[PDB]
Length: 99
Length: 99
Ligand code: HEM
Ligand code: HEM
Ligand code: HEM
Ligand code: HEM
Ligand SMILES: [Cl-]
Ligand SMILES: [Cl-]
Image (cartoon, rainbow over all chains, first blue to last red; front, top):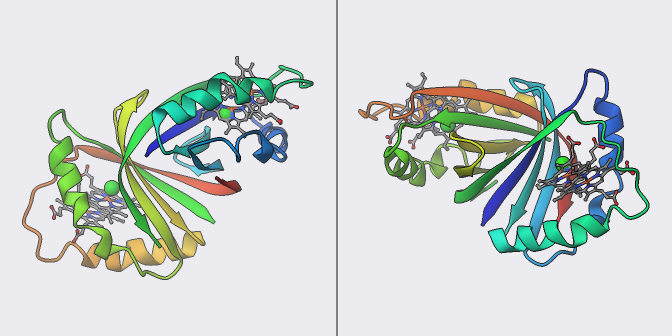
């Protein structure tokens, strides 16, 4: 599997607004083929960016979602972001250990 | 829950040695109270550091592990580190969505 993290820069005080924009977003991705899950991570120490951490069975599965269903999920939405920058961090899972 | 990511810097070519070291490390953290799991992420694009992504029911559970077992787990090892630096990134899980 692969991990794709969108590391989002958020202006001071805009944390709650950004989090609210994610609150009903599950429908936009949860059903996608090869999707294994995602977490929105609020930074607490050592990082100022929010991490949107997504897990996929493959790179192609993420790309299919990004190029199709993800774009479609914007219909009817303002495209005015509160984030001031974003960086995509891509990784391959080399080890996974359960609780 | 909380997420603690250790972002470790690894010289070129040490990736395999670092990964081999993590391959036999599950025992050092699994079963610890409040531990929910971890992944070793090998960087592919956008990042040069390995991400050690760990999940915990609370910060206290993470501190209890880091302060006791994790230290104890070094006893008997005679290898020098291959990592040259590390940064702990700490997060609160705000949203969790399963696939
Ligand atoms: C992991 C791959 C992803 C990438 C590359 C990506 C990419 C982006 C980019 C480039 C932006 C614009 C941010 C800016 O203006 O600086 C954005 C915003 C956004 N994305 Fe993601 N995204 C990803 C995953 C997700 C997922 C899984 C969700 C939710 C299901 C999501 C929901 C959002 C939302 C709600 C915004 C609006 C942020 C705002 O208004 O400031 N994204 N994304
Ligand atoms: C320049 C590029 C982008 C911009 C400016 C942008 C902007 C936004 C904004 C402002 C929203 C908020 C909608 C609202 O508040 O109602 C949103 C939602 C979202 N974005 Fe984007 N985004 C971009 C690219 C991306 C990409 C590349 C991805 C994933 C690969 C993504 C995934 C999402 C998702 C899943 C949502 C939530 C849709 C929903 O609430 O139903 N976005 N985006
Ligand atoms: C400067 C500080 C540290 C140094 C120089 C260091 C060095 C090392 C080295 C060389 C190993 C090799 C084990 C092997 O090759 O088999 C190791 C293992 C390990 N380290 Fe550290 N470490 C440090 C701090 C930490 C911290 C702060 C944690 C967690 C809170 C940690 C957790 C671990 C764990 C869980 C193992 C694996 C134990 C095992 O597989 O038996 N280390 N460390
Ligand atoms: C998330 C909290 C963690 C922290 C704060 C932490 C911290 C550290 C630090 C400071 C080092 C020394 C890096 C250096 O010498 O530059 C290290 C090395 C290491 N840690 Fe972690 N660690 C964490 C989690 C873990 C876990 C869960 C494992 C495995 C179960 C692990 C296994 C190791 C190993 C094998 C090394 C040696 C890397 C090498 O060979 O150079 N650590 N850790
Ligand atoms: Cl995002
Ligand atoms: Cl580590």
